[PDB]
Length: 33
Image (cartoon, rainbow, N blue to C red; front, side, top):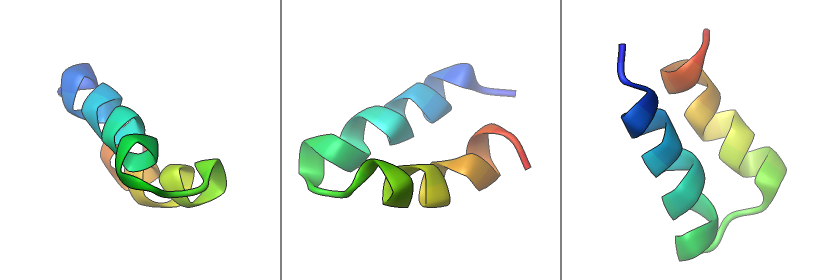
């Protein structure tokens, strides 16, 4: 597992430019699916 990679995804998603729901859409497979 890698909670760090998850946190990176949820961080960089909005840092770059994506809506929260889109962030969840992309990072969810990584974090928990």
